[PDB]
Structure formats: structure tokens, C-alpha cells
Length: 66
Image 1 (cartoon, rainbow, N blue to C red):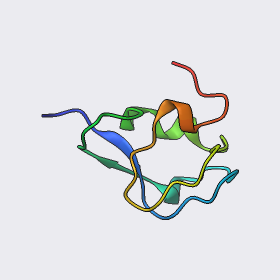
Image 2: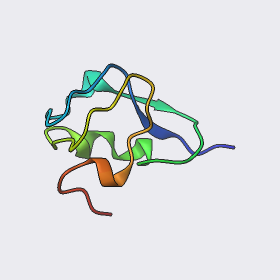
Image 3: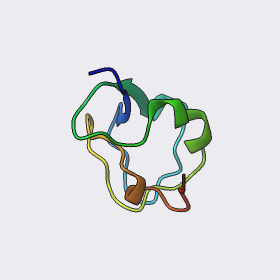
Image 4: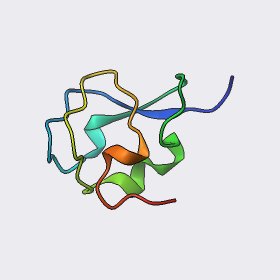
């Protein structure tokens, strides 16, 4: 399996604006937001708390569409 996802590099509190320190690239299942998209996620808000190691999904990010 080759496709990497965005995963949380720290706990991301609810309603936090994302920064680059918060986002790592990992090959995980199920697949989340493509890791390719990390620079476009900066300053977008999360609508729930995202624990460390959690795969960031499209429905967790306010305003995200692809």
C-alpha cells in the first residue's frame, strides 16, 4: 500500500486553526485526506478534537472540499 494520509502530529483541540507542525504524512487505513493536501489545510479549522495519531478525514475540516 502506497497512499499516505494526513495524521495528527499532536492533539488538535476542537475549533483550532491548523498549522504545519500539527500534520504528518503516514500510510494508514482507512485512508483520510491525501498527504499531498497538507499545504492547503493550513489555517483551516477542525470541527472536533483530533487526538495524536488520528487520521484527518474530510468531514473533520470546516470548509474542506476536493
